[PDB]
Length: 129
Image 1 (cartoon, rainbow, N blue to C red):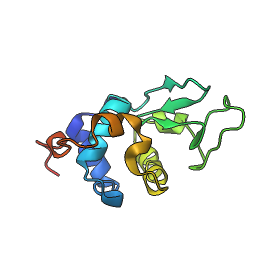
Image 2: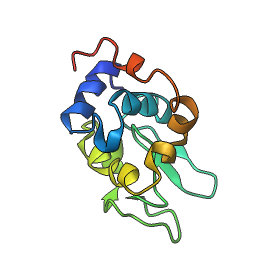
Image 3: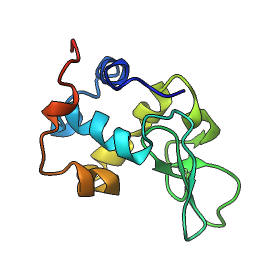
């Protein structure tokens, strides 16, 4: 399921994501926009062996569980398949353990590299948030 930019902005904002740990909602639609390009089931294989899942590309080494990463954790205690989910609740109740942990959104490299230091607001620009 490809989220519409604003359909997503809403959804995120629905799960109290909009500004969680000081990240303006525009900071999540953008990270998502690149991490996954808005595809709820965006799977990108990671070098080391790990796997980035769903909308906000949450690595399976650490957060989700996939059965294929010898010695990788599952803190959010969930099967990544549950991240690919069309409903993005999980991915978000999960993209908090990723932004609350300590490194902020610099976890999502695509945000750190493509968003961090830009017009994030210009990402919800149209969104009736």
